[PDB]
Image (cartoon, coloured by chain):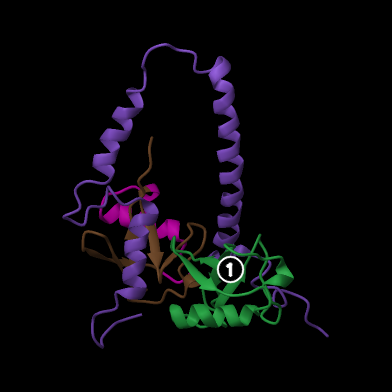
Chain colours: A purple, B green, C brown
Amino acid sequence: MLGLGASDFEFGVDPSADPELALALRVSMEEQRQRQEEEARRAAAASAAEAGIATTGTEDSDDALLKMTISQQEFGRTGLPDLSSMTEEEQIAYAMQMSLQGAEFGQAESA
Amino acid sequence: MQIFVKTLTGKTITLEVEPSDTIENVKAKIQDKEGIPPDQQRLIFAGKQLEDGRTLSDYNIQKESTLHLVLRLRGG
Amino acid sequence: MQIFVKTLTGKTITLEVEPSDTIENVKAKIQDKEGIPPDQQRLIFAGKQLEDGRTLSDYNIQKESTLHLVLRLRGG
């Protein structure tokens, strides 16, 4: 035939054409990292007890201020459509929800 | 068997199936539970799309297996 | 092409561009009207994130189209 070009492969070759397939392969790689980190960190903790966490006292307050301050700030007040709490994907989750699930206008201009 | 299917919204569905079930049958199960059409639902596992004629055993799938669901669109 | 860009606060802007303009160019236009840098402006449409290298025609964006505007928020 006289084909062979940018037609036989337009979905299973370039992820830029479909972010659903590009995100699917990104979710699989992230899973392998969870098992490689949860297991890599478990071995780092058992070894830290020998020559890593050798301290007789208490010094776990610096992160408590980072977690306690962000735990109530990141998830505390929600009685308003705040934007600082929504990241670039969280804000996108709201902006994209209106683009597909927010066409409540009538019959003048809608996509 | 009870397998789980994760979607692109941090949501996983639990469907009871078997190793001799066809991928097309699984897609029909997610369509009746959610409503999405099967021709659009794409079952990808370990970074590989599954065929509709093949079953879950052809891809070495067991119970509590998490599959990656995707949406096919010919527009953008 | 007179298009409209809605924001999260509830304000739309009239951006006069063409179907061959890049998303980054549109962000610069909003930076001259509102007064915000382009690096802090994302263009979403049809539940899809528009790339800075792609143009308006790549996303089937026509005239009088309502494009969603997001605000970049990272550390630093």
Q: Position of residue A82 (x, y in %)?
A: 22, 52
Query: Quarter of the image holding residue C61?
Result: bottom left
Q: Would residue C23 be seen by someone viewing this image from the given angle?
A: yes
Instruction: Tell which residue pokes out farthest to the bottom in this image.
Output: A107
Total numbered labels placed on residues in the image: 1
Residue at figure coordinates x 61%, y 52% from the top left: A29
**Quadrant of the snapshot with the N terminus of chain A:** bottom right
Q: Position of residue A80 (x, y in %)?
A: 17, 55
Q: Is residue B28 magenta?
A: no
Magenta-colored span: C18-39
Judged from the image, the secondary structure of the residue bearing numbered disc 1 is: helix
In terms of depth relative to the viewer, which is nearer, B51 or B60?
A: B60
Residue at figure coordinates x 38%, y 12% from the top left: A57
Tag 1 subunit:
A
Instruction: Tell which residue pokes out farthest to the front in this image.
Output: B1
Q: Is residue C62 above or below residue A108?
A: above
Query: Quarter of the image holding residue C17?
Result: bottom left
Q: Position of residue A88 (x, y in %)?
A: 38, 52
Q: Give the residue at mark 1.
A: A17
Q: Position of residue B47 (x, y in %)?
A: 66, 61
Q: Is residue A84 above or below residue A28?
A: above
Residue type, mark 1 in image: Ala
**Quadrant of the snapshot with the C terminus of chain A:** bottom left
Residue at figure coordinates x 49%, y 66% from the top left: B7
In terms of depth relative to the viewer, which is nearer, A104 or A38?
A: A38
Residue at figure coordinates x 37%, y 76% from the top left: C63
How packed mark 1 is, by other alpha carbons closer than 10 Å (few <14, some 14-19, many 20 or more), is some
Q: Is residue C31 magenta?
A: yes
